[PDB]
Amino acid sequence: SKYEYTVXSYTFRGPGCPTVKPXISLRCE
Image (cartoon, rainbow, N blue to C red; front, side, top):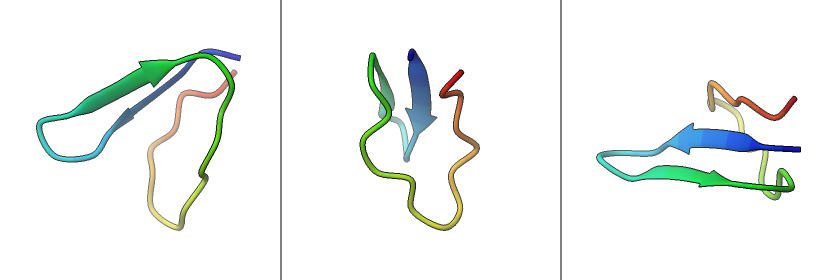
């Protein structure tokens, strides 16, 4: 519903979880 994924110094915050690759500390629900 509202994911936060910090890859580098680039915090990707937005609705609807797209890629779930092996090694994200994902904040999907």
